[PDB]
Image 1 (cartoon, rainbow over the protein chains, first blue to last red):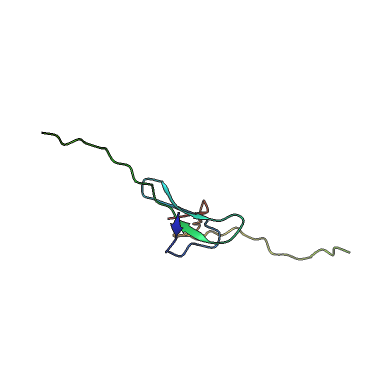
Image 2 (cartoon, rainbow over the protein chains, first blue to last red):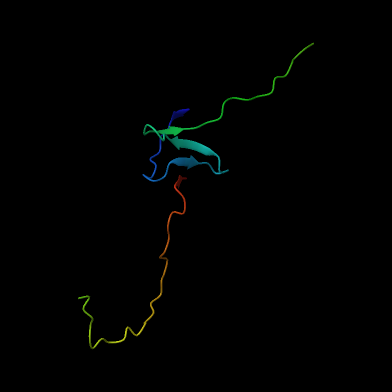
Length: 49
Length: 31
């Protein structure tokens, strides 16, 4: 969860990505727009002689 | 009360072209 940068429309609450993923949110209880990004995920690979 | 209007011209229902009018934001989603 990170703070959101770009200015939302007052009615617009959730920011959407090109692939329709949600990358920003509006707090329902408090009021602040937050940027949303995925947590890290890779694939471990073992190098070995 | 609710007085009526007398000697009223018909509306005549003329038409004008809409152009690029009638656009709304369907959802409250920022993009």
